[PDB]
Length: 122
Image (cartoon, rainbow, N blue to C red; front, top):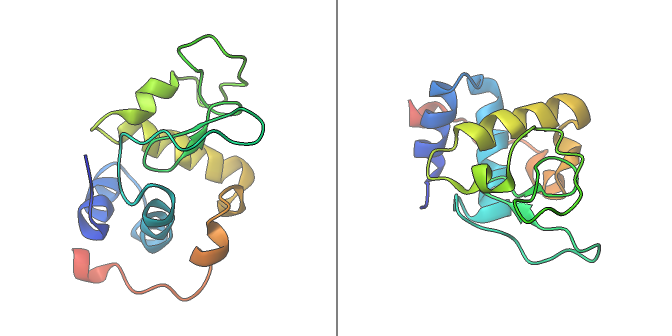
């Protein structure tokens, strides 16, 4: 359903995400999905859709279960990104960050500043 900054921070930390990255991740999530896990974003101009809490693109990162060509660089169904369990979205988001950086998110431009500490979450 819907996370809050801290619940998401807590879960991602739990999943192995460095606290250092959490203000950024949660900023991204707020911008991308308002923390909603089950969102498929509006169709992009190229016919793709973004999936899940981090709005991961179904052309590059996950495989549409509808058969649509994808690079599926995260090696998962896009549906896997819509689950209440953010594990898949977290791993995939982390892989994307690893490959293309935060800059892979359009919303990064909002999230690249001096974000508040995540410490209040712990």
